[PDB]
Length: 230
Length: 230
Ligand SMILES: Cc1cc(C#N)nc(N2CCN(S(=O)(=O)c3ccc(NC(=O)c4ccccc4N(C)S(C)(=O)=O)cc3)CC2)n1
Ligand SMILES: Cc1cc(C#N)nc(N2CCN(S(=O)(=O)c3ccc(NC(=O)c4ccccc4N(C)S(C)(=O)=O)cc3)CC2)n1
Ligand SMILES: [Mn+2]
Ligand SMILES: [Mn+2]
Ligand SMILES: [Mn+2]
Ligand SMILES: [Mn+2]
Image (tube, helix red, strand yellow):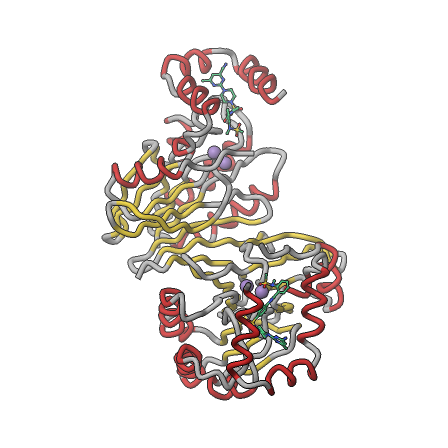
């Protein structure tokens, strides 16, 4: 089985979500062929040089999974787009592109965070375009850490769902009948049409009282919710 | 594993849902310790004497599961409250009460359809009280089938969510930390408090483009959505 998760929004303020994630990495994840994390692993990221102890606890847990023989992969979310090659090295995770077309036991699946599909949000997309410009990233990252923290705090003081056409267009660009994403925090299986055939869009949930994952096997694709009852 | 499903709303008009259900009974269900169907198996029911061919195709498929060594159980929904002992015999299913407290590998779980929790719907509950009165049922069922059909058709020409307090009260009456239901067609895992401890309410989805089930093992409880991709 290949596993997909997203929208953990991990942070110092929410230790119970972190514990649920650590339990998942130590249990479920070890049995998998691979683990894909489709963005918003962290609630925020201002650079890999951040000494936040949570960051190292998380990289250390993911690295254990990778070292146990289960490749882990990452696609950036809107929250954690500044996750970089240094974290990748610490965690053993491989950074992937904003869209990837996978071959899962012969089934072709498109994966992404899902924020790019939300084309009705002009505000978000203007923001995204700027923070995805390399020289704007390298500017922000060249500031002293204490100034990056002030910038984030000052920003602080509902997520728009996908545009249906944008979904079709993406599945048609990749010629696939399967899409897995998060971002929208609306866990669901959807049926549609793409490439003249039936297609499915499987949406992951955010981690709060529950976790969620998509499990892909040779014959099946399942969206699973689990409570943190341990 | 023990499996829970609900809200299939099976009907002549929707053969693709019926095929998804038959595939599930022939595959997934055969591997289980038991199968519980928590109501709204059928979109409508006007009595067991109805010769609708769908009714016999469904009973025959469920009976195969029971005969293969997997007990099947049923709790009535609002739609199919007139399902009776004759169908039970045809299907091999055991009829259970509107609330049951189960022991699943040491875990105590409350199961029900969920309509009784929806105490904000005065209209529904007035209806329910009447159609659950035995002598009102036996009156309706004593009519000729052709008159029962007219009555249903004439009735034809959104589902209220649960009352949060009603949920707590039910879990507290049974002294349980686990509740599984359907009815509301809002598949989700919810955390709450009952009996002074953390509790979980696991809600099944309706079958249309997807199926859903709750899988209970010694150590885990999972809500699973599956598309009908075969
Ligand atoms: C390179 C660059 C330049 C400048 C500078 N100066 N600033 C930064 N960020 C880095 C990321 N951090 S963050 O992690 O705390 C963060 C903060 C806000 C968002 N905002 C959004 O994602 C967003 C924006 C618009 C509309 C919707 C949005 N999301 C959907 S939402 C509702 O979750 O916030 C994302 C990450 C804030 C500072 N980066
Ligand atoms: C014993 C008795 C007496 C009389 C007579 N005369 N009539 C009957 N029924 C049997 C059931 N059939 S049914 O299966 O077609 C059916 C029809 C309507 C409902 N209505 C509701 O469930 C309902 C009613 C009020 C508010 C909400 C409701 N549901 C939530 S909903 C929106 O799904 O319909 C249920 C079953 C209709 C006739 N039974
Ligand atoms: Mn998110
Ligand atoms: Mn996001
Ligand atoms: Mn229903
Ligand atoms: Mn119902």
